[PDB]
């Protein structure tokens, strides 16, 4: 999932842009994925 | 054959040439009348 970032592939954001921009995008990846874990994790705890 | 072409089509109707089935000629672009600007939106210039 894009999570708002320009692509869902980690490297393909990099090699497209100069990193000082990627630092911004990779947030919207991390902020997305990190969340998606905490969703999944908090699920498991409840389900556990 | 695109860059150094003598007479371009006008901005309103621009001639579309597919560069295809070849090995990158980008190295020869260095020494020339070159470009007023070289701006890569799709990838960083090193990845070319
Ligand atoms: C275009 O012509 C210049 C010489 O005017 C040359 O240096 C350059 O390599 C040419 N471009 C390509 C892609 O061959």
Image (tube, rainbow, N blue to C red):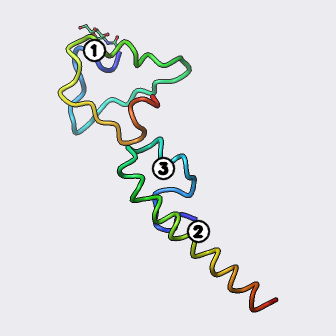
The residue sitting at the left extreme is B36
Place of residue A46 in the rendered image (x, y in percent of width and height, measured from the top left): 75, 92
- A45 left or right of B28 in image: right
Identify the residue under disc 1: B4
Mark 1 lies on a secondary structure that is loop
Identify the residue under disc 3: A13
Distance (Cα) linking label 3 and label 1: 32 Å
Pinpoint the chain carrying mark 1. Answer: B
Q: Is residue A4 above or below residue A35?
A: above
Q: Which of marks 2 and 3 precedes in the sequence?
A: 3
Q: Which mark is residue A15?
A: none
Mark 3 lies on a secondary structure that is helix
Mark 3 burial class by Cα count in 10 Å: few <14, some 14-19, many 20+? many
Distance (Cα) linking label 2 and label 1: 47 Å
Identify the residue under disc 2: A33
- A1 left or right of B47 in image: right
Q: Which of A27 and A4 is in front in this view?
A: A27
Pinpoint the chain carrying mark 2. Answer: A
Mark 2 burial class by Cα count in 10 Å: few <14, some 14-19, many 20+? some
Tally of numbered tags: 3
Mark 1 Cβ and ligand 1 under 8 Å apart: yes
Place of residue B19 in the rendered image (x, y in percent of width and height, measured from the top left): 46, 24
Asked if the residue at tag 1 contacts the one at tag 2, i.e. Cβ–Cβ closer than 8 Å, the answer is no
């Amino acid at each position: 999932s894009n999570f708002g970032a320009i692509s869902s592939v980690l490297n393909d954001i990099l090699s497209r842009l100069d990193p000082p921009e990627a630092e911004v995008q990779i947030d919207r990846l991390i902020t997305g994925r990190l969340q998606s874990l905490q969703t999944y994790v908090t699920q498991q705890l409840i389900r556990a | 054959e695109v860059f150094n072409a003598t007479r371009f089509a006008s901005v309103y109707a621009w001639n579309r040439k597919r560069i295809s089935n070849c090995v990158a000629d980008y190295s020869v672009l260095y020494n020339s009348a070159s470009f007023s600007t070289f701006k890569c939106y799709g990838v960083s210039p090193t990845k070319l």
